[PDB]
Image (tube, rainbow, N blue to C red; front, side, top):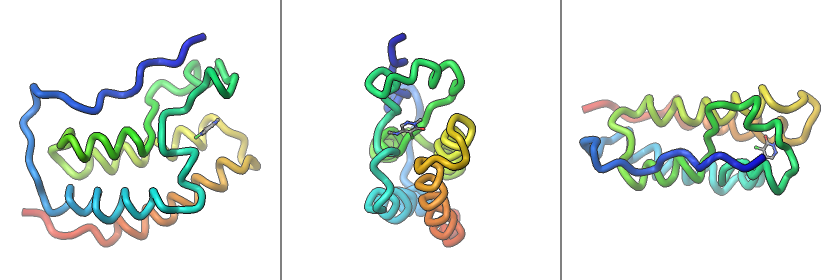
Length: 127
Ligand SMILES: CNc1cnn(C)c(=O)c1Cl
């Protein structure tokens, strides 16, 4: 079984804007998570072929990862901050759905989610 194509990261047919919250999601949220000791498994799409996990994309129909989110933010793919927050939420939920609770990857995802929630609880004000 092949990997699926990665999620779309640009689209010239959508209007674009810079906002306080979107800037914060890249400059603070993404950048801070990216530096975490346990960020590496979440920095790019899950390579189910190399991991020999052909059931990964049988189970996970909405893949998401921080590499994709980073590109989306850089490419102004999101109009609303919540679209980006939803992508982070999806990334964590995918990990929890697919993996066994005792797996290191879940411990890692949970550590990142803790940091994520700390950062989004300090989201700046909307225009
Ligand atoms: C490299 N990241 C991985 C690898 N395997 N699985 C099952 C995952 O959920 C993740 Cl995030």
